[PDB]
Length: 165
Length: 163
Ligand SMILES: [Ca+2]
Ligand SMILES: [Ca+2]
View (cartoon, rainbow over the protein chains, first blue to last red):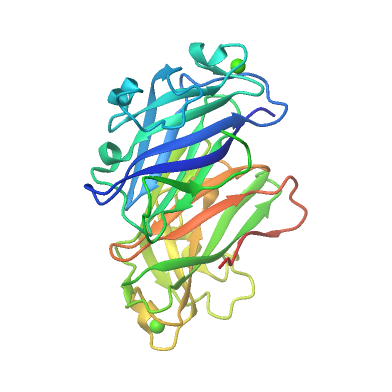
C-alpha cells in the first residue's frame, strides 16, 4: 500500500491582487511506500464552483534549502505554473530520484501552483479549497483548507501538518 | 453573507458490491445566513483520480422522520440518484422552504448520492473522498472523509460535525 501524504500547504499573499495568488503543496510518501512516479500524477482542486485538473509541467532543484519558494527571480520555473499545470520543487531528496520525477522514501517535494492563473483571480479571505494529488499508482495526498479571514503577511500557513519542509 | 456547512456524512455498506454504495451528506446553513436556493447547486466529488459533478434532481419529504435514510423502497427518489444527480431530502424544516429547494435558518437537508453510480463501483476501504457542495450563492459545504479499514456494519459514520 504505497501512497502520498500532504504535509502542509502555504500560500503567497499579494496585496495588490487582494488575495492568495500562489500555493505551495508539500508532499512526502506514506511511511513504507514503494517508489512512486510523479510524472503522470494529477492534481485536482475544487474552488468557487469549479473543479480543475493540473498536470506535471517539470521539476526544479532551485527550491532546495530555500526559505522563499514563491520568488520567480530565484525560481524562474514559476513561469511554467500556468492555468493547467503544476511545477515540482525538490525540498529533500538524498538519492536524486525527484530529478527523474520519482519520489521515494524520505523525499519531500513541493507542488508549485499559480492560483491566480488556475482560478483566474487571487483567492480571497475565508475561501474553501479542496483537492487530491493522485499519481497513477497508489493512494493520494489530500488537500483541505479554508483561507484565513485576514491576510497579515506575505507567506501564509494554510494547512498545517507536523512533518518538516 | 451566507453559506452552507456539512454537519456530517454517513454511508451504506453493501456486501455484494464490496463497499459503500450510497452516501447521505447532511447540510445546514451557517449562522446568520440568508436563505439559499439549492436548485442550481452543484456537488463536486473527487475519488480515485476522477472529479465528478452532480446536479440537483428533486426534493423529497420521504426522508422526514425516516430511521433508514438508505431504504430505496421507502424513499423512492433514491432512483433519481444516478451518476450525474443527487437528491435532496428534507430532514428539518419549519416553513416549507426546502419543499421548493430553498434552505434557511434552522433547516437540515440531506443529499442522497449513489456512490456506485457515480464512481462505477462501490467505495472500498481506506479510500479518500473530497468534495464541495456549492450553491450559486454563498460559501460551500465541504466533504472530506477516509473510509474505514473494514466495513463492520451496514451504516457507517464517515464525517462528523466539527467547529
Ligand atoms: Ca529520493
Ligand atoms: Ca425552512
